[PDB]
Amino acid sequence: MSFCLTELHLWSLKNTLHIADRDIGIYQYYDKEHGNLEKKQKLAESRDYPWTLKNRRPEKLRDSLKELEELMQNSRCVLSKWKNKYVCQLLFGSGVLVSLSLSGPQLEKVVIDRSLVGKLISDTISDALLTDSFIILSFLAQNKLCFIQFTKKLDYKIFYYEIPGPINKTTERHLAINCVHDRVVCWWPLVNDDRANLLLLGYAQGRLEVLSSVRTEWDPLDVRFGTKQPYQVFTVEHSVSVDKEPMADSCIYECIQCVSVTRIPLKSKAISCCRNVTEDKLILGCEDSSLILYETHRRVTLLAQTELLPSLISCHPSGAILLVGSNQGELQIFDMALSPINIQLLAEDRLPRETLQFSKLFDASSSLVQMQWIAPIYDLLFLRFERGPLGVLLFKLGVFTRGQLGLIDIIFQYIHCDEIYEAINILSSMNWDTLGHQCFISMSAIVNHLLRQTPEREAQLETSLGTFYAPTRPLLDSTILEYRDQISKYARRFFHHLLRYQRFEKAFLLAVDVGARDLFMDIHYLALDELALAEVARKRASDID
Amino acid sequence: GTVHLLCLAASSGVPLFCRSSRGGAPARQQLPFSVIGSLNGVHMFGQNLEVQLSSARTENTTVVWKSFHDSITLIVLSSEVGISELRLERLLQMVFGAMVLLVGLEELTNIRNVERLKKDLRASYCLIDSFLGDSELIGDLTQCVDCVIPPEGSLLQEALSGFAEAAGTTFVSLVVSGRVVAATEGWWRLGTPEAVLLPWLVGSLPPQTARDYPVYLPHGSPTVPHRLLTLTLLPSLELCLLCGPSPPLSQLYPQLLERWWQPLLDPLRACLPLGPRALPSGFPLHTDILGLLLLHLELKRCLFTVEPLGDKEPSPEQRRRLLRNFYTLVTSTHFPPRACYLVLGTEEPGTGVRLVALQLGLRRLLLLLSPQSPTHGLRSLATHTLHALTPLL
Amino acid sequence: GLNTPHIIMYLTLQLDSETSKEEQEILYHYPMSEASQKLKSVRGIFLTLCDMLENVTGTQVTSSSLLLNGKQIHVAYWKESDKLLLIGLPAEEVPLPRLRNMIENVIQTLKFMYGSLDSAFCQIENVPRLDHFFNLFFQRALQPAKLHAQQYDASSAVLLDNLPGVRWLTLPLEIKMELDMALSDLEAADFAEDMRRLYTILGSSLFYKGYLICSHLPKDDLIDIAVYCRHYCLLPLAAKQRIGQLIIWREVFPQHVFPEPEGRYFLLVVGLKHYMLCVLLEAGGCASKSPGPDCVYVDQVKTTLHQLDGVDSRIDERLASSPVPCLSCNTLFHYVALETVQGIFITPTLEEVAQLSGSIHPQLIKNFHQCCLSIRAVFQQTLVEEKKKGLNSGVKEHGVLFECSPAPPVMAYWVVGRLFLHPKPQELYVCFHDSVTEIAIEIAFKLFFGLTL
């Protein structure tokens, strides 16, 4: 019954976007049951989210956006990126570069620069990288790496570099960029029977260069740069076992250097993946609607079933929430223990549902190609469709939380909804250590909830304290010592809670684990009044004295 | 639930009647005699100790006592949820006023002959049961005259008032199913229980082409045998002429009536099919409206409608109940630039009705709305609806 | 004034009125003054009805209206065991919906302090204590002017006394955890001098300046302690005055899948410097087996308060650092949020409304609370109907607008609240200008989401 409440802003002006009347959860820009539309106008205008866009100079926002919409429908987009929450650029295979700026969830500015179109000779750009100083371009049928350097920050110079890779006529060359702009990679899903399918590229001194190359042992599902030791190139390679069954191989390269690999068995072949912002969690979408999470610290593979094929996945930048998206518009929310979370669009009545259907959003054939939490709060999720509308999904993530949605906030909501079993699985996924502070507070919320109110709940109390007392993978000792005083106090209250009910044997075992002076006497006086346990408790008391 | 009403002569302690209803239906069940004597004996005990008992209520029921003059105690027991003393007090004012209209304050006050009252009040039982059960009338609860808006109000009103001198009275009205469609200025100056009770009596009585039912009008004529004459022209449609003892029965002759009412046949027929609704056919209501209760607070007249939607959720019987119950709530907030609303039902949409009310310009409108209605849009909806109804009252 | 007629009587319903003992029907009454005496003379009315109307109908009488001396007096009934509690108060000060809740709070308090309602009255030794209790009760209900920014609580009381909950202060987590740890530090404690423990600490709760801060105690025990503290003005005393030291010791009877263990309970309340800390102790159960305070439990609560005094300023900063969500003289004006499952209200602080002050403001606040009581009565009927169905198994929103003005500015003044039932029984109340087209779901989500005690 726990859910997140959201509102969608659809930036397209198309009349094919058949949002239902009184569907207050979705807003659309308008060009220059009607009473329900007017009522939504009143809400939108009482709010700071205008029903229509300015057509007035200098911005001419209505017209500049309309040209962007034409560009989206008539051309493939090779890149979309954000510089900050209000700044976006997107690039097309047409060679047109577009930048837009936002206020709140709403559009304020559109700029279209078509001057690059007649200057860049190309065949089918498949990919691009964007920085303020330069753009990197890649093509489906060429060994050309096209490099653009801006004299601004348009006024620019065009350079070309030769790509060393094989089969230039058909191979799709993917690109990625470090936050340190001095390093870039190019890669392709080579299948064959000179050898490299990944290049290490540098940038320095106004020039692009090739530094080195590797051949991976399996053809990658993804290639990404790390945020730590950022030059390091992480991959996820799907592979076939000698068992003739699918696996994911998380190879890492420092090139020819493969510094590490981890093999995770799969129920079915992976179709997508992403990394959690802490990088301690790898999530793969897979065939037959399966979702697999590997926790490196706990060294455990968790499985879950999903109601949609997870072709697109993206982590919330707080790291606490995963989104799973179908290309067909189904959306599902998961926590970091892979429990499903209900989704609701704003409405006058309360209706949490396990998935959200964006099939309601339009009658368009256009498919979802991107979900992205907007890069630097973070309550805005950018959506893009190919040959379809752009827009942003806003998450109304609490007032007292000040819009935050950490693992701690999910725990509090699960306490509020009494979803305790799920809250404990999350607590287990915290891995303590670096996250121990947030984990500790989440434990306290769970234990206080249960101590204030049955053997089923005792099992939950045992497990929650168990996440510290019996780790699936051991805690660092300094983590133990940081929380040792408070965890023991929460356990002491549980011992007393158990004694009030006729369950002395388990309470006895906890008294042994705690080992406090005279603690055993609390078993003795009750067992004294199963009467045999009273003498055992006397013996245990003597083991401290 | 069930309802019981008991009446006793305070001067002797002897019960005058007991009436009851079950499910809103007339019922023959009466309370135990020792209970009845104790219900009044406790009231008279308070009387001798300078205390007026006015109510009691059990978890299942509400019980109300009233003392009228020195002679009448009315005790009402209602086993229904959401019943309150205001509804019951207004009911007992209507019942007592009905006792006044049937016998006057003579006999009814300073009671000596109990046996005469036992026989004389029997006619009252039919009207009392009609009040105890459900009907598509709100005047008994609002103390406003139940009303209808005709498509041709100026045509009916001029012909209705032009007849008043010919009728021998300044008090004339046109009634559909207990609702007033049109009435004269003299008719509109009738006092609160008086203006409501008169059409209630008319609607509760079996139809006649020429009724003559005596009415000892409480306002200025409580001891004088004024009489109410009514003329049925179409089913549930009748004229009322409110008369002193002086006006002849010849005033009811068709030879005088036809020239005042025949020209009005079209709008008279137009008001007939309204039944439970009060607005003229084709009125531009918002489609989410399930019904209205429109009060005019200065004019003391109100329209009552339940819209005949085929969704039947709530049923018309429930819609009548909902508007009556909402009014009772409205009078604990609005009654001595404001609005009120309720949303009924379970967590899912489609589970219950929206209700709204607004007071503007000394008229107050109550609204029963479809489950699909937006809850944020209610005020502007209420504002537009009032503006459409503004010209009518 | 004190001359306004009111009465409490405890009456036997074994109506052997023919016997020789004078006023044998009365087991207790208060006040003794003349204003009550006429009400006392009509005591036979209640006796007649409390027998008769449950013979006529399937249930007990709950209330009645009498007129005396031109006053309308509402009289509440409670037939606990063929033995009746009766309370009569003027309608002029006490709305019927307020009275029926007030008798319920009296019934719960009597059972809480004395175990059972009938025996509390049958005990002659409890008479002067009952007289003191009812003296306080008939000042709160009848003569509110004693008040034990100005009269903010008095305008609040119209609504605050009716809700099934406790005024509570929302805090940033950075403060909340010091406070929760301090309660855990107390609840885990067992100190002496090898010995049987004197009590189990069933739980504890902390208040600051009339606001609940946090609790380790169960909800049901929070409700009973809060009601007791309302009747003795303990919470408002902390809110308005600096208490040097308060100590309260009482035996209590807080109702208390294995069965609940047998035992006896003690309520300890200690407070200093606007803090008030309540501890509920259990004799029997895991512990030894009426005594006064054992001193050691008083020392432990006082030590806990010393720890809490290190963060009082941090709380005051939260009280002082603008309203959350912010309020205008954004056009939100007021709110009350209640989770009925926990003893929590969330409200604008006294400091925050005083910060919002103006000539219009104090009138608007009184209107808000009074309208919310009228709303509560509607929700309470619904809650009872739904509870009956829930018991047999083992309405949703209300609001009003008032245009108000000091050629002054005219402002819209919505008062709205909503009742939720299924995942939780919870109630929201809000107040805002019509300039903002608010959705109750959006606000209820924002306020309740991430909320925890």
Image (cartoon, coloured by chain):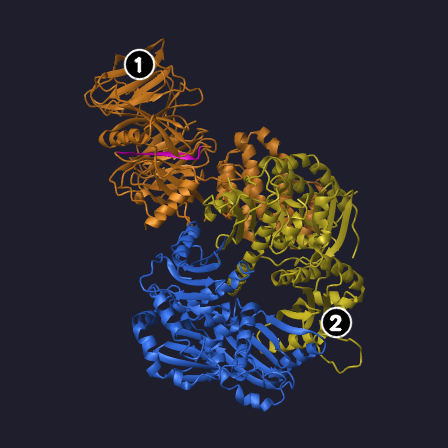
Chain colours: A orange, B blue, C yellow
Q: Which residues are magenta?
A: A378-386
- As measured in the structure, the alpha-carbon distance from the residue carrying label 1 to the one carrying label 2 is 99 Å
Asked whether, in this view, residue A465 is left or right of residue C112, the answer is left
Q: Is residue B28 visible?
A: no
Q: Nearer the viewer, residue A299 or B290?
A: B290
Q: Quadrant of residue B222?
A: bottom right
Q: Is residue C141 above or below residue B85?
A: above
Q: Which residue does the numbered mark 1 point to in the structure image?
A: A155
Q: Which residue does the numbered mark 2 point to in the structure image?
A: C38
Q: Position of residue C351 (x, y in %)?
A: 64, 40
Which amino acid lies under the numbered mark 2 shown in the image of this protein? Answer: Lys
Give the residue drawn at x 74%, y 80%. Answer: C17
Q: Residues within 10 Å of mark 2 (few under 14, many from 20)?
A: some
Q: Is residue A374 visible?
A: yes
| Chain at numbered mark 2 | C
Q: Position of residue A133 (x, y in %)?
A: 36, 15
